[PDB]
Image: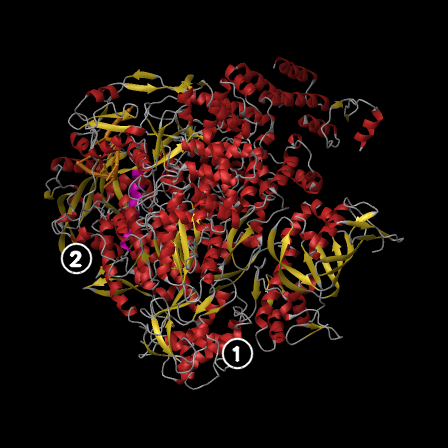
Amino acid sequence: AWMVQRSLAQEHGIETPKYLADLFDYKTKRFIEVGITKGLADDYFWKKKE
Amino acid sequence: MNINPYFLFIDVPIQAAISTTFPYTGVPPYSHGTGTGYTIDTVIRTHEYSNKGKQYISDVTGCTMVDPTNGPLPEDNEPSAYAQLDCVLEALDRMDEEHPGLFQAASQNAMETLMVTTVDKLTQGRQTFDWTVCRNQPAATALNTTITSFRLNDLNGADKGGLIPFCQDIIDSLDRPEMTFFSVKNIKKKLPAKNRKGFLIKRIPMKVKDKITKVEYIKRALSLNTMTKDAERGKLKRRAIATAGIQIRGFVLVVENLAKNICENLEQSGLPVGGNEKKAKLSNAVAKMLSNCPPGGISMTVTGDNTKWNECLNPRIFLAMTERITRDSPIWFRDFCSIAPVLFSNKIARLGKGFMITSKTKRLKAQIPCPDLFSIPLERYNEETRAKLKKLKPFFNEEGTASLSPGMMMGMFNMLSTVLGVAALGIKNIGNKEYLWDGLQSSDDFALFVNAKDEETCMEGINDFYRTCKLLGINMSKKKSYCNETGMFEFTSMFYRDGFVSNFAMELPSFGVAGVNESADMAIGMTIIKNNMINNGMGPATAQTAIQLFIADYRYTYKCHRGDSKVEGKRMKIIKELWENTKGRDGLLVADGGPNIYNLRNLHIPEIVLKYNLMDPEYKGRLLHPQNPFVGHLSIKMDYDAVSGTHSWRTKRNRSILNTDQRNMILEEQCYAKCCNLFEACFNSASYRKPVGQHSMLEAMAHRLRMDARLDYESGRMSKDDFEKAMAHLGEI
Amino acid sequence: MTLAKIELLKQLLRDNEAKTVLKQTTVDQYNIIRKFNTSRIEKNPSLRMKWAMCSNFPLALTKGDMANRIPLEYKGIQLKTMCSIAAVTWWNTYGPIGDTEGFERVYESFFLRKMRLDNATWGRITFGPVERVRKRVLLNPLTKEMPPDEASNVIMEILFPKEAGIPRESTWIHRELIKEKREKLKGTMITPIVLAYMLERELVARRRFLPVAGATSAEFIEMLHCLQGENWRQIYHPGGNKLTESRSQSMIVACRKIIRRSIVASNPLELAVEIANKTVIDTEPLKSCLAAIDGGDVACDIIRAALGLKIRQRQRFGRLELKRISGRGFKNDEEILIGNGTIQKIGIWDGEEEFHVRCGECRGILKKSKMKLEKLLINSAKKEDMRDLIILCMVFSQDTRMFQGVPMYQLQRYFLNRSNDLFDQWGYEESPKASELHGINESMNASDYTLKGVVVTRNVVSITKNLSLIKRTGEVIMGANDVSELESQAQLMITYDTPKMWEMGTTKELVQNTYQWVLKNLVTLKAQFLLGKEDMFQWDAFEAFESIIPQKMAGQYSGFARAVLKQMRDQEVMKTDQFIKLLPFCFSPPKLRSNGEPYQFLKLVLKGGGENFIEVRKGSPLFSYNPQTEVLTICGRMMSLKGKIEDEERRSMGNAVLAGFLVSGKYDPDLGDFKTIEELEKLKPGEKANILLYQGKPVKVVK
Amino acid sequence: AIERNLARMSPLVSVTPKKLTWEDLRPIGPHIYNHELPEVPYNAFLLMSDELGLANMTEGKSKKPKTLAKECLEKYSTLRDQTDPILIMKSEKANENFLWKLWRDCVNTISNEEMSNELQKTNYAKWATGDGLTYQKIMKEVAIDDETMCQEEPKIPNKCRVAAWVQTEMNLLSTLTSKRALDLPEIGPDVAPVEHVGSERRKYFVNEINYCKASTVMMKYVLFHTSLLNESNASMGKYKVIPITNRVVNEKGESFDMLYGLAVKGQSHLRGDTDVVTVVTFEFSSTDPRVDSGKWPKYTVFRIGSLFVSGREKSVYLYCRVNGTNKIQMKWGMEARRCLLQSMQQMEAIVEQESSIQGYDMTKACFKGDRVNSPKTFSIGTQEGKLVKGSFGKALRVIFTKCLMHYVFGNAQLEGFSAESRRLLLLIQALKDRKGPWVFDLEGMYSGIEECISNNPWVIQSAYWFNEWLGFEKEGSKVLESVDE
RNA sequence: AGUAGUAACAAG
């Protein structure tokens, strides 16, 4: 998973994320992080932003 | 006028001229034939020292077990194995009192190391008794056969990565009713020969399969393969040494790592310190005892030596040592450290090849194996061997092995035994008498300092030390040990005389050609000369002569004499052409018949780097061709600095044995070689760094090569076809 | 390449044996199966090499494109079949001329060894004693030192950036070094595994114990074999640049070693100037080092003042660097219980002191007393600089809160990593409510509950004859006895451009050289002793010997030695071996008892360790005599006294042991035990006593 | 628990300390003086002091060994073409005709125009090689049923007495000659002053050893074992002749090529390290074996002619012997050059310590002497029961010879002797230094030493010399006991 | 025979 993350980031010409990413769109050239909360979405949203 | 070499000692003292008394230029004594006579001596003598204690038949293995621990005290100066538990524990309590957090801190360091330690850590212990094939193999080879064998009986602890689940499977494999495993078997194929009988047994080996019952497997796991020690220095008669299996190795590492952490902190320890750091530590330890000595009293040093070290020391005492040491640690780690002593306590000793019988009248010989050892009248064996086989009877097993509960044969517990030796040194006084002993310990060899008001009390202090050591299972050799006033002594072959004097003859065998290769041995040869100038007291004249004598031995070995010289040979015929072709002759290496530019100042610089500016451009290009076929598969005991040129080559594997065609052996070796090379092609860091992953080795490569294909297509390396062919090949896998 | 790997992977997987390996074997187990060798470990490689060279085809060739360039034979010489040793020589003579570009950048570390030797200038050789102290040292100089764990991650980022894994903080820290070596190591065609080795040898430190004498630095340790033996010295000046920190240590060691000599002689300031003028730290003089470097210690300021330069009142505590505003401190060896539960001898600093502080970027002012942080005014900066500044000042202050919450450099290294133990045990208080002043919490952020005695603000001599620096007011700031007595090893070479360089030497060097000077001039010294009364005792050579002896016992030994020698002078009982042994102790001004008699002694102790002492009655490690062969043993070295011993000296030793004592007869059991020093001193004149010279030779002696 | 156990343990368990004295140090190895035992025979691989090199003149550049041996024998044709010899001495189990037939086979095979040095596998060669003398490997089932087969009682080394020749070997090998044998290669140029001092020291140290007899003998072993190891691998099945060759240079610099004799290599399928290849050594010598008959029971000596040395014909004999060696002994022969380093380091250490005393390089002062200092003298040996002094250079040659004898007579007996006797040596040093040494079981030390004294000439002669040296120290000890008291 | 020395090799 780290080999995939580094190989993508190195090829496209971007900085590698510090955490382990969950997805990556090829057209956007942007890593994606998925989260499945129970209660409010915005509460879990801004916790990940920190 | 008759010359006398000993008369040198009139003018010069003996420690100053100690190098002369070490005949290391001579040939060391090699063992001939079988080692069964030497092994049986050790088995008899081990039981000889413990026979007064408890005897009982083991219900697990079905073997005669002797137990001298908490046995009757000795009433003579013979070697006693009769150690007393309470006396051992008091010496350890004394150590724990003087060294407070050390017992539990060493346990946690060993414990936390154990948790991080992987299974591949085992593959660096030289020879190991491979229980599958029942002969000694390398640590990596013996481990890999055990991992594959364990998978056949549903034991995939090795797959998890850590050393703990592998060691969990070892103790659980003892409970298994049957043990299926991969083994090797011969193929006795007949051929015509021109030698007496007129035939030839061409043995071909191959990977087969076997099954062993619960009890018979337990014996193999507890077994120690024995053999005679070749090239042993400073001794008349030869002796046997054992080599244990892969099972016990994991547990011994932890017990030794525990005792290592204790030893480092102990002020009177010889191990694990070595070289200059030892010489630093010991000279400090001596300096204290000289200035500790009272005014008018006497400090006396005993040049120590213990007899029958491994044979008297019992595993049951080493079990008690681990139980005391790991007090505050959890129950799982207490149980882990306890396993290694338990296996040694119930061990079995293999007895080598056997004995040869011959008829001089007929001129015929025959090896009798250990299973068929008593299948013959004992009168037909010789007078000395007859007495050994009679004493072996009670401990002898049906499958041609010997039970051996006491002793260690060749005990791996050096560190833990050094702690037990220091434990005796830690008492210092008994009965509040007018003396104070201390010393130095390095497994078997020791050195005891004894401060007191008069020398009559010093000897009584030495007598009290002698007697205290008997209670721990340590027997001081009255024959080999001796004593004198402090100022000079000997310890681990290092001779002291108001300071440690140099001994050049100890390192003299290292000065020759090492046996790796031309490029490496040159770098080694100069480094050995360079180190001995610093440490062993080699002067500049002798250092420069050692340079000269190395190049001579280097040239005669590798057959690479000076190009200008008229020495004929297979290599030399081409060297003479190269000497003519090359302009910058100083640029040529000694391996290509060039001149030796090395001197005292430039021993530390590699030859290729030294001569770089004097080389020709065509010569250096060929010498440093990046993809040359001589430089094989490299991967990052001493180390050296050398440039990887064409002279960095590899020797052939030793396969040509007594008409033994080993095609199938090498097929398995190539099968792993092919898989590992392709993994290194995919993952380039695998040569440098240790790869990690419990997942499949194919899965790592498959997912890697998919991303290689995708990024090559989008960036524009591969065409539209090559990507679709590449993606197709992965779809199958 | 990707297509070639996949095609080989497929064709490998077709084989059922290889398929069973790749599926079952884990990525952990790759390490095990790489080292799978079926044959045997070679127990005699030197033999088997010499054996293999005699046979035809010992070597092995790697199967490839270039391997087929070598023919099956060449001029009746069978090259390959595996191959012979002639195949290797054929390649270098008539092989493919490959690409060797970037070879100097890959093997950059090794070329730096060459230019250090090539550009070096070799000084004098001098034969004489050398005290080699076995200390831990760096074998080779590095590009940038790291641990093995951290270094491997930097090497990984350079060579194999796709296979690095989790990006560590070290990637961000050592980013300029990665970028540099990335650009250098690129065009080369040499294998990655070879590059990784060369990066490791210039990053991972090789530190080993070696016998050192006056040269600890790596550029010296790589030449250590040529620099010095047990019985000779070689002056060497390695080429290239040198670190300022490496000059700073040897500058401190230089000034300390000058002071220890000059204290003894009359007018210390005169010698201090005389020697410090002609000292050379490798190549530069001591003057230039003291002028250029803005650091040093107590000793450097004294020499700076002696030579006549500004005195940088500065103290470096590892990463912290202080400058003195006001106050003086004095050291006290006290035993403090550390919070973990251990007894440790640590030198506490007494009195109130005030320092101008600076730690990297961040700056501030310090105020402390005996074991307390009274105040700590600091400025705003980066988080790592402010955190280190507060921690290093707390450790430097030697507060009880620091100790009760777990020798000074060991506490530094502990609290640099594990700071959470300190900040909790320290405590907190209310912040200052001024306009410019502010407070901060544990995480280096602006807070109301600040640390106890920590404030963050927005705003930013003549020398005596006896070596003590006095202000114009009269108060003194440095002192002769205010220097450390730790005689550590110098990082760089220290040459004293003087005829008397030995005088700044080690204990055993001075002990050996002094007795050698006595033996050479034993004809004139022994002759003048029956003429000149107190003319010989005060000789130039014996000043250097007194600097070895501790100041407290120096006078007592002179009173003792002179009286023992005066027995041999006045009365007819002269010993030559004893005359040689005691004469160097007589230079110091003598210090007798209240009675008028001198202090009696068994052994005369010298500086540095328990080895260094002279025995008055017995022999010792430094000094002993053998009357059988007339061989005087000094520090291991043996000199002869033949031709310079009297015919009536055949004479008991007890006559020249104790001052005011002589041998009447021999051991008399009726008197009883052997009388100790205190018992012997307190006897009446004209009273008998039993004495043991050396275990075996008892004597009856009378006062 | 310790103190309770020690109190209740038997007092019989004790260290038994006894303070050592000179009277307690009894002469080691009493049996070596008993004339009822046979005197230790010569058992080295080649001859040493008794050697004779048929010196042929050359350009001073390397040639083939067969061509060299051919040209050496050509120049001394009377000895080459001898077919009617005189048998002077015979070994017990030797054969006169087979050894002589084999000697002629060597001389004729080497003299011929062909390239091959292979000897024909004759009845005389097969005996001296030991053809078919091994026992046949039968199955275990057959051997168990056979009642005649038994485990052999192992041979134990003989108990021999002091032979006078070992003293003579030590004397003659230590003596100087006009012949340099060493093949020391070049080194780099001297830049540093240390390298200038070292290279200046080598002129004194190396020439002292190089000109001596022991060094010429050392280089004979080295070059023979090198070529013998090569033939052993390269010609396993073939019986081959190998010449005992050595190159030599004199004081003026003209090169002589020495032929000490010829030697027959046997069949050498050497798999194991300890596996043996028989080597039959035919060597020239001026020594008459009848003068000291007890030296030569292993050898079969033929009188083959004479050569005019001085003003009269000296008899040239041919010492024939069946000998043997193994892969290890051959390898340690090739690394016999290190005998220089062991002796040269030991004596340079004294020069360095002496340089520390006087402040300058005391190399010349030790060897020759100078303005200030006398020459370094050592107690070299005895003469009619009194000490004799020798120069610095002699002591170096003595110690160099000592290190060569460690190789020539290197085995388990020398290892155990030198190791166990070293304990006793250090105790003598303590008595010399007046440290008052103690011992726990002195007969235990002697047991370990004296079991190793058997049939090794160097171990026996060392035991003789140890006891002689011990006597002279005991005489000097009477001075120290009368000091102070 | 011989090497060698507590048991082997002297081809398998």
Q: In this view, does D290 lie to the left or right of B136?
A: left
Q: Name the residue under label 2.
A: D310
Q: Which amino acid does label 1 sit on?
A: Lys
Camera-nearest residue between C526 and D81: C526
Mark 1 → mark 2, Cα distance in angstroms: 80 Å
Q: In this view, does C547 lie to the left or right of C337?
A: left
Q: Which amino acid does label 2 sit on?
A: Ser
Badge 1: chain ID: C
Q: What x and y, as percent, mark residue D188?
A: 46, 52
The circle on residue C544 is: none
Camera-nearest residue between B106 and D83: B106
Q: What x and y, as percent, mark residue C377?
A: 80, 55
Residue, far bottom: C531
Mark 1 is surrounded, within 10 Å at the Cα level, by few (under 14), some (14 to 19) or many (20 or more) other residues, namely some
The circle on residue C591 is: 1
Q: Nearer the viewer, mark 1 or mark 2?
A: 1
- Residue B355 against residue B492 in the figure, above or below: above
Q: Principal SS element in the magenta part?
A: helix
Q: In which quarter of the image is the N terminus of chain C?
A: top right
Q: In this view, does B321 lie to the left or right of D171?
A: right
Q: Is residue B37 left or right of residue C150?
A: left
Q: What element carries label 2?
A: loop
Q: Determine if residue B217 is in view.
A: yes
- Residue B617 against residue B692 in the figure, above or below: below
Q: What x and y, as percent, mark residue C110?
A: 56, 46
User: Magenta includes D225?
Assistant: yes
Same-chain check, marks 1 and 2: no
User: Magenta includes D314?
Assistant: no
First to last magenta residue range: D210-229
